[PDB]
Image (cartoon, rainbow over the protein chains, first blue to last red):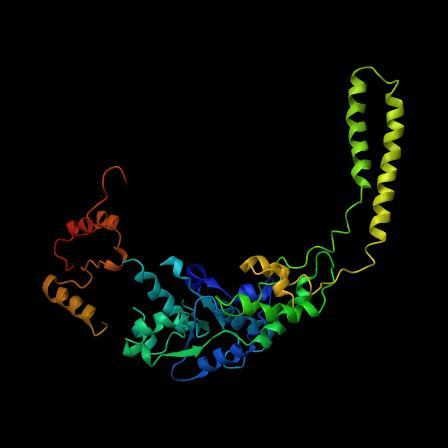
Length: 309
Length: 62
């Protein structure tokens, strides 16, 4: 069960087994690419070539997701996924010698990195690199032993259409708290303008940025009371505090009227609240395209009139 | 490594000291920190190896 690897790193099959995180949507193309490289006899160490932030983290997350879903092939069946973070880096070399021994004996441990030359030369460790392109051509290419052992994988930003399916797939997972209705028009409109203005962090992280504070002026805006409960609740507040003072002051001449008034106001508050929600829960507050572009107006400073065309 | 260096050390002690188990094996892999030097030389005062073992068996191969 590789106890050393389970304590010095983070296991991915345990996290994916519960499925408490959002599923990886839109990276289905890379799912078949990672397993394909691991099945090759030569160069069975794929490397996530790309800028840091393009979505390389989701590539490793989706690899262990197929194990629970029984979508991985027989060659990659029932194999745990282990990732070693760079923040736990002499005595440093004394720990990596024991971890590699357990991987060879088990035969189902897949390393994930973000000394080891003899280990990679024999292909004993099937580590998956995650270094950027700039650092891959400076430390890995300069060494001939690792040149024929690490197979670069082109992991770049997805297409515009591919990002659209991400929002639709996760839409059902975004409505479970207040049961609101989201229009389908805002889904396609959240990817056209995303690349127009924000083009400095690549897809899909820069793509899903328009729907953060775009259309939020409809649903709860009508849930307010137009000078209805602003005064009813205030009357209840003053009666309660004044009632307690009259008890200790031996003044029950006016306290008797206060109790009846307070009870009547409490009944009225419940009736007013019930009628408010009954006439509003039936209607649905869907999104509108006229307010989607309002959030991007303040990100860059472009006037809303110029954007709304 | 593994070519038989350990066997050569054991054979050397057998023909010289007349014994094969009279070897004090010290592994430097466990001595990496600065405080590790104060372990084989002996326990420093106020806190609580190699010196203790070699004293009882002066005819030993390290």
